[PDB]
Amino acid sequence: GTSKLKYVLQDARFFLIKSNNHENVSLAKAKGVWSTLPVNEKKLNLAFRSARSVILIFSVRESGKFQGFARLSSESHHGGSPIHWVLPAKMLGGVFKIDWICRRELPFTKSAHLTNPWNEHKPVKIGRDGQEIELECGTQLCLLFPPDESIDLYQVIHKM
């Protein structure tokens, strides 16, 4: 069902994350971590304190698709286990822990009806790394993804 998913997305904030390569998104999916540039790290730390759920929606540059979405489970922290990001290292901020909600892909062709008020109503696929996606557009975008039946949102609800 979609009921627990809708509950997780209630009053959430959404941010577009753009990765230059698939390798880093694969690492994030395997390890439950993400790191971004300091300008976006600051935005995400502020958002994490401000909302019940902060959702990162991932897109590998030039792939034509989103690769999934995840909920921040922490603010960024330093020192843990130098993640072997395939860089396109110090200019990177701290590490956020994330819980994946969906590891399935969504092609941009499926989101063409969704525009983001916070980016001049351009299609939601369009945006720099860290672009905030308004609540209604972000909710509808997440609901377009194929259900990920490997994920049990019960534990995610408990972190809220």
Image: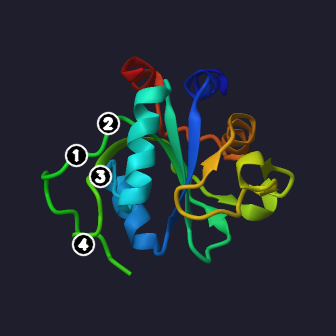
The image position of residue 78, as x and y in percent, is 17, 51
The crowd level at tag 2 (other Cα within 10 Å; few <14, some 14-19, many 20+) is some
Residue indicated by mark 1:
77
Can residue 102 be seen in this snapshot? Answer: no
Residue type highlighted by circle 4: Ala
Closest to the observer: 14 or 47?
47
Determine the residue positioned at 22% across, 46% down.
77
Instruction: Look at the numbered disc 1 and give the secondary structure of its residue.
Output: loop
Q: Badge 1 local density, few (<14 within 10 Å), some, or many (20+)?
A: few
- Which numbered disc flags the more N-terminal residue, 4 or 3? 3
Which numbered dot is residue 66? none
Can residue 127 be seen here? The reply is: yes
Q: Residue furthest bottom?
A: 88
Marks 4 and 1, the one that precedes in the sequence? 1
Q: CA distance from mark 1 to mark 3?
A: 15 Å
Q: Earlier in the sequence, mark 1 or mark 3?
A: 3
For disc 4, the marked residue is 89
Q: Position of residue 14 (x, y in %)?
A: 58, 42
Residue identifier under label 2: 74
Labelled pair 2, 4 in contact (Cβ < 8 Å): no
